[PDB]
Image: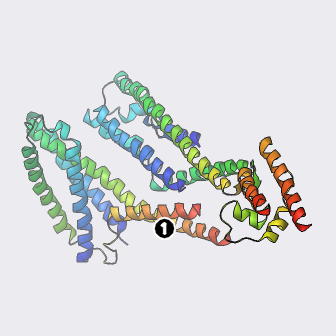
Amino acid sequence: TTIDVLSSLFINLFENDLIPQALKDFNKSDDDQFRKLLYKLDLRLFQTISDQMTRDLKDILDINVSNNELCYQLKQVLARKEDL
Amino acid sequence: PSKIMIGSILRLLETNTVSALDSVFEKYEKEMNQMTHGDNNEVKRIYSKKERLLEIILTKIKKKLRQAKFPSRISERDLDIEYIYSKRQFIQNRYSQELQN
Amino acid sequence: TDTYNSISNFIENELTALLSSDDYLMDDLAGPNEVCRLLKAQVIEKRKDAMSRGKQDLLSKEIYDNESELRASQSQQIMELVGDIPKYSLGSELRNRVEGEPQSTSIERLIEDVLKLPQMDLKVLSEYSNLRKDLILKCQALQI
Amino acid sequence: SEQLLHNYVSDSLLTTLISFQEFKQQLQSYTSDEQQLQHWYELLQARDARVTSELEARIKQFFITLRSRLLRFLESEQLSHSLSLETLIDALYKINDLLQ
């Protein structure tokens, strides 16, 4: 009853809070390579977190639906076995 | 919201985030060293500083997620990507062998 | 066989993993950080559901159907070729002795089996015919 | 089905997914120059080919390699249903010895 509230809230959190947090810090640090670094790796971490959780939540949904779907096709295969 | 539900989300959030943190560190390590003076120790210290800061954020999510209304029925045994991926592999093998028979 | 698993692995790793990670590789090649950050947006969101596990499973199933039909035809066009006699067309004693020790012997069974042997390389055919005729004469001589 | 995979990989190319004018306008608010964009786009075509040619090689070898194992697998069972006439003569010789 709350699956795409949960995933949407997580995805919303990353682009709304995480991504700008490192992005603004990454933008600010042009004077300091070592701090601009920490913020660039944080920005890459938050971008990869963004894309990774987006298609990982897509993956939990897709794996669930495709598992049910493959179960049904397996029923079909068993029916063929019985006929033979 | 059930403590089991809150935890199961926390396990997904924390475990996935660290898997992003270690993966990005090793993926980008080639452009990491020239400006950390090539010190893997400093990289580890840099990891620790961001780990606690990420934990500070993650704990911020926890103490804000705990009051977020959720049910209790969803199982923690299925709320993990790797387990359902292994299930995908298992059913795939079942499918193939049944077809050939 | 389990060729469905083979094609599934091929599409998921050799193709889907390759090009999905090639999105990130094109990202790294273009950088111009925001270039790649956008590159991962519009082509990928035009790519959505064309690389889903559902779509991968569907296309792999289609490929499996194609290959199964093709190998079925390939088997069908070799069912008929036999440069030999087939099994079940020769008496029990012969189909036993030819492949293993019969575990028992009976001369009467042997003669009423060898009397059934049909007419037919050319040297094998010649020795077959001569040996069979000699054997028929042998059992006739017995009976007499 | 080599052509199926060839179509899928050709469809999956980024250059296939974005035209130049398309490629321009998502990047128009961002990049500086059309010709500089074209450099990446002609790079995008001059690049997106060599994977395609590489992708052709692996799908081609993939589809023929499985055909080889299927064929020999199918051929093997036929050997269990036919009897070598030479072995039949090998048996008939000893049968004649018994009768003798």
- Farthest right residue? C144
Nearer to us in this view, B13 or D22 = B13
Residue B24 appears left or right of C2 = left
Tell me the quarter of the image containing the C terminus of chain D. bottom right
Percent coordinates x, y for residue A75 in the rendering? 57, 70
Percent coordinates x, y for residue A15 in the rendering? 26, 52
Task: Tell me the chain of label 1.
Answer: A
Q: Residue at x 60, y 67 (%)?
A: A76
Nearer to us in this view, D91 or C72 = D91
Dot 1 alpha-carbon crowd within 10 angstroms: few under 14, some 14 to 19, many 20 or more = few
Q: Residue at x 34, y 78 (%)?
A: B73
User: Above or below — where is C18 with respect to B9?
Assistant: above
Q: Is residue A49 visible?
A: yes
Residue C44 appears left or right of D72 = left
Q: Residue at x 40, y 42 (%)?
A: C18
Nearer to us in this view, C87 or D28 = C87
Residue C124, quarter of picture: top right
Residue C124 appears left or right of A3 = right
Residue D50, quarter of picture: top left
Nearer to us in this view, C64 or C1 = C1
Percent coordinates x, y for residue A24 in the rendering? 17, 44
Q: Is residue C46 visible?
A: no
The secondary structure type at the circle numbered 1 is helix
Percent coordinates x, y for residue D45 in the rendering? 44, 28
Tell me the quarter of the image containing the N terminus of chain D. top right
- Label 1: which residue? A68
Residue A34 appears left or right of A81 = left
Q: How many marks?
A: 1
Q: Amino acid at mark 1?
A: Asn
